Image 1 (cartoon, chains in turn green, brown, cyan):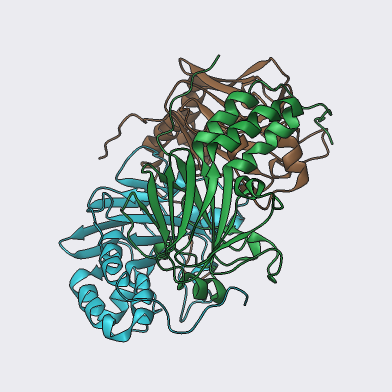
Image 2 (cartoon, each protein chain N blue to C red):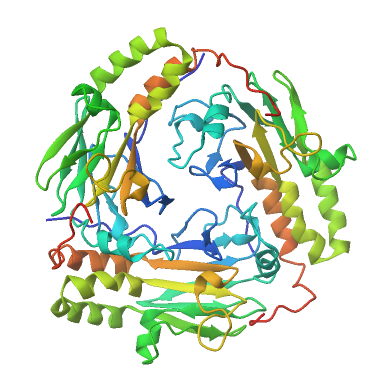
Length: 203
Length: 203
Length: 203
């Protein structure tokens, strides 16, 4: 059985405008980085969304992109990940790991006002969930990828209360993948066998 | 005239869900790799499709992704490339190079049941076809890029017999590009001149 | 305040077919490169569009791709960038920096016939515009990203005179980003504060 090597990048970030992916995926090699609305294309610690083009872009998205500003600072201390709102506008985070910690609904979206920060991920909690997931079968273990994913919207909120009901309805959002947790999940997933119900070649 | 340097990656692989590209392109630097449905984001020998997100994903695709499992092993011995079905579900391959070898229709899709393998490419055959393609003109030489491309679907078949008629109708498939052959083709294409029928700036 | 490091790549190039992005972004590390319709996947000085696949491609695009040929040579001398038409078919360039230099409309598209070249960018002019942009506010400075972007179509023209009115209506085009200018803009943008009109979390 297989070999693992420590991820060179602790996370990857994908930017979206509504339901469309925009720009290349950003890979973070440093423990602290900022996703902002500016234009430096060569800072390994900055994912600058302002330089990303989209000929198909609409006015609402353009308008919102102008308010990203300093955006969000993403960093980790030990086994915990945080998101700090550097922007003059708030950011909205949907983190299953965070939501479960507070007993909130899994799809809960938490508002992080300017100047505030939130613990979007805790490894201990994830490791514990992963450990108990085995007794649930391939089914539950496979779905844990969602716990390694965190989505955040700049300026516009979505979900309960807000008119916008889904992340794809927001003008500017990012999707963060925590690579360490994903590798941890892989070590378990590869030993959980295959699904129960049969998937034919024709249906 | 120009200089060539040996490709650092023998192939590139693009993943798709129906007619939409999902995730970044994978580049293989090792002679053997596996494309599976798991989640390690840091193994140079594994293209793990399970960690790839798609907020726009439908139930059929999600369902099928759960059955990719160990997926397919792609490797080359000398000038020959093979695909082995490690998955508990079959994979379906459409390789023009393979199809021609057996006299099958160019768009033929070959089923590779679990545990089986198929020679999806042979360089000698390609080189020979390329050599005779010159007498066919820019036309035939330009179309040889198709010979350097191989498409494979996980779990679901397509083409003759199956309901699904095109690769874009399958939930999860990959597109492999053989870089050595592409460079070989380039050396010829750059010397084949331009098309015959005129392409205006207005039509 | 922040640190900048010289860009390892002087520019990035994105290829499109109509309104759809095709292929990975190309990053240039050498002062001279060519974007052609051929197939070498391993030359750091060549962005070969001919090897790029698109299962969703239409006949018009396929037809045009066959006429890209030697394509366009993009290179810089000092602080000036040029585009040379190596292709047997013309290329059409939309460069705000070039257009302003000649007093043409910002969206003007300039035809570069085979064998001809055009100065698509001049840093002195941009730096001067950037300097005066400050007195215009965040508004005008933010829009300068457009000056760092240049779009070019192969074979087919668009805009005034031609039937095609937008770049997204052309079969094969590229989008060039000048990284040095973008970093220069960043140094100013980060000091221009935030927008005037308020952007709420609900609208």
